[PDB]
Image: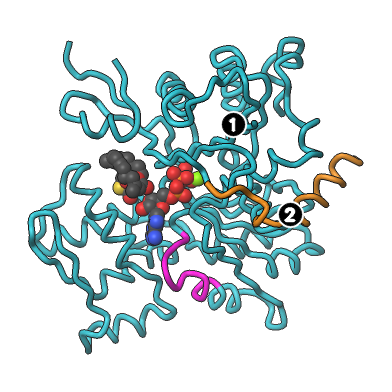
Amino acid sequence: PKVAENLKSQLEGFNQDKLKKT
Amino acid sequence: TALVCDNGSGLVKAGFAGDDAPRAVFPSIVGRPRHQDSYVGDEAQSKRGILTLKYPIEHGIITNWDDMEKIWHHTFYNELRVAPEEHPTLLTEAPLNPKANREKMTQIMFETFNVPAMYVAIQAVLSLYASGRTTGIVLDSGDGVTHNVPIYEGYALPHAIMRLDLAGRDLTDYLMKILTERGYSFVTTAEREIVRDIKEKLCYVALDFENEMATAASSSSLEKSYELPDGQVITIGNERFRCPETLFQPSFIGMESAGIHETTYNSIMKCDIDIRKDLYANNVMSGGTTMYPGIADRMQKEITALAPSTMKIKIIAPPERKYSVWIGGSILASLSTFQQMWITKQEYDEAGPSIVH
Ligand SMILES: Nc1ncnc2c1ncn2[C@@H]1O[C@H](COP(=O)(O)OP(=O)(O)OP(=O)(O)O)[C@@H](O)[C@H]1O
Ligand SMILES: C/C1=C/C(=O)O[C@@H]2C[C@@H](CC[C@H](C)/C=C\C=C\CC1)O[C@@](O)([C@@H]1CSC(=O)N1)C2
Ligand SMILES: [Mg+2]
C-alpha cells in the first residue's frame, strides 16, 4: 500500500535523461 | 545489475536496467537441423537452408517452451554475456497471458537459469510507465498482436483489454499480396523481409483514406521508388497508405474485427465512467507498428469523432516507442522502491510458481 504509493511517485517523477547511454 | 527482457513475437529486446535502450535486439526465431542442434536469431536465418525455423512466441503468447528456453539461453549467454544466476531479471508478458504460462516462465527462470530474483510485467503497462504515467490507455502494436490496455493507478484493467490478432507481420503479408498481384515475385520468408523493409520505409497512415485514394488516382505526388535486391526498381503510390489502413479497416485482409480506433473507444467504454476523461487525455502509442507517419493524427481524428464533443483527447506517440516497453522495464527495475517487489528464489523455493500472480 505504502510501497505502491511510493513506487507510483518514483515512476511519475522519473527523468529518462538519467538513463545510461548505451 | 538487473536485466530486462522484452520477449516479442518478432524481436527480443534485452539489456540492463538503468540503460536508455536495449543492448540486444534480435529476431525471436529458433532453428533446428532438418536432416540427421539449435541456432537462435540471425544465425538461424543465415543457416535456414539446413534448419527448420520457428517463432516460439505467437501473437505475444509463448507457445513453444523448448524453443523459448533456447531464446532465453541465447539472450543471457550470447547477447548480453552474463551469468543469469547473478542478475535479477524482469520479463515482460502480453496482456491476457494465461496464468499457467506465467507460472511456467517463473519455473524455467528459477529452475533452469537459476536467477536470484525475477518479476513479470505486462508490456503495455511498462510502455505507460516509460511515458511517466500510471494512468492512461495504451495502444501497443508489435509484430504478432495489437492490444488496447486501459490502466488506472498502475494496474491494467483486464475486463476492458481489447485484442486484435492483426499487427506488423500481417501488414507485411498484405503488402506482399498487393505487390505479388502487381507482378513482382515475393514468396519465401527471405523475400518477405524485403517487403517488410519497403513497408517500414515507405508506408504511412492517411488522415483521410478516401481523400488520399483520390490524390493517388489523379497525381503522381504520392509515388515513391525502392530498389529491390535484384536491381528492379518498384514504384508504389496508394500501396503506401492502403497497407496500414488495414489497422483501421481490418476487412482489408478479410477480418471482421473493428479497427484500432474503435477498439480504443470500446476499451474506454468498458471502464468506469469516472476514469474515462483520464483515458481519453492519455492515449499512449507503443510498438513498432505504431511507427507509421500519420498514425497519431489519424487516431486523434477518429477518437474525436467517436468521443463526446467536449472531451479532451490527446495521443502520445514518443519517438522511441519501438522500445517503450523495454525502456519502461529499465526504469521500473532500476527504482529503489521496486527492489522489495522482486520475487526471490528463496520465496519460490518455499511457495512454488504460483507466487508470481
Ligand atoms: N518504422 C516502421 N514503420 C512501420 N512498422 C514498423 C517500423 N519499424 C518496425 N516496424 C514493425 O514493427 C514490428 C516489430 O515491432 P515490435 O518489436 O514492437 O514487435 P514485437 O514486440 O516483436 O511483437 P508483439 O508485441 O506483437 O509480440 C515489425 O512488424 C516491424 O515491421
Ligand atoms: C530488422 C528486423 C526487423 C524485424 O522486426 O524482424 C522481426 C523478426 C523476423 C524474423 C524472420 C526473418 C526471416 C529473419 C531474420 C530477421 C531479421 C529482421 C530483423 O521476422 C519479422 O520480420 C516478421 C516476418 S515479416 C514481418 O513483418 N515480420 C519480424
Ligand atoms: Mg511487444
Check if residue B341 falls in the magenta segment.
no
Residue B18, x across and y down, in percent:
64, 43
Residue B142, x across and y down, in percent:
46, 50
Residue in the picture at 68% in, 23% down = B117
Q: Amino acid at mark 2?
A: Phe
Residue B293 position by quadrant: bottom left
Q: Quadrant of the C terminus of chain B?
A: top right
Q: Which residue is mark 1?
A: B98
For this view, does A4 lie left or right of residue B226? right
Residue B166 visible in image: no
The vertical placement of B295 against B190, above or below, is below
B330 or B217, which lies in front? Answer: B330
Q: Which residues are magenta?
A: B290-299
Residue B249, x across and y down, in percent:
41, 65
Same subunit under labels 1 and 2?
no
For this view, does B351 lie left or right of residue B87? right
Chain A pictured colour: orange
Q: Which residue is mark 2?
A: A14
Q: Amino acid at mark 1?
A: Pro
Which residue sits furthest bottom?
B218
Residue A19 visible in image: yes
Residue in the picture at 33% in, 67% down = B203
For this view, does B73 lie left or right of residue B286? left
Q: Quadrant of the N terminus of chain B?
A: top right
Residue in the picture at 47% in, 60% down = B290
Chain B pictured colour: cyan
